[PDB]
Length: 69
Ligand SMILES: [Zn+2]
Ligand SMILES: [Zn+2]
Image (tube, rainbow, N blue to C red):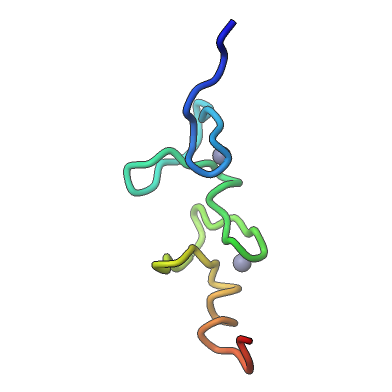
């Protein structure tokens, strides 16, 4: 029984009958979270950066921080 669909691009798991699609790509509500605090970006206001996606929470801190590294 070969059971393994492509699914999203994050966790690579089939998308339920109520997920989300970004940039013509299969994404999940949990996978569509910032690569920092893992916040639900879907529906909320987020910023897509060439590198990765950051929620208004992290973004603000990134664009406006004391020291990056
Ligand atoms: Zn996923
Ligand atoms: Zn975040």
